[PDB]
Image: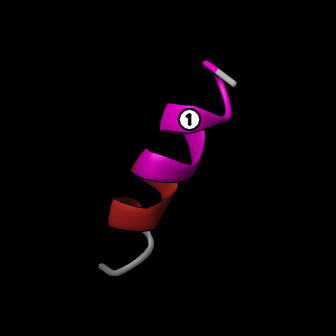
Amino acid sequence: EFKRIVQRIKDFLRNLV
């Protein structure tokens, strides 16, 4: 329940940078 919030951001900047 605390991995979906971090997994949604880690791939939010790793796909644009």
Q: Which of 16 and 5 is in front in this view?
A: 16
Asked if the stretch drawn in magenta spans residue 5, the answer is no
Q: Nearer the viewer, residue 1 or 7?
A: 7
Quarter of the image that includes the C terminus: top right
Q: Where is residue 10 in the image (x, y as percent from the top left)?
A: 57, 50
Asked if the stretch drawn in magenta spans residue 14, the answer is yes
Is the magenta region chiefly helix, strand or loop? Answer: helix
Seen in the picture, residue 11 relative to 2 is either above or below; the reply is: above
* 11 left or right of 14 in image: left
| Rendering quarter of residue 5 | bottom left
Residue on which disc 1 sits:
13
Q: Position of residue 3 (x, y in %)?
A: 45, 73
The chosen color scheme is: secondary structure
Write the residue at 56% across / 35% down: 13
Write the residue at 44% across / 65% down: 6
What is the magenta range?
9-16
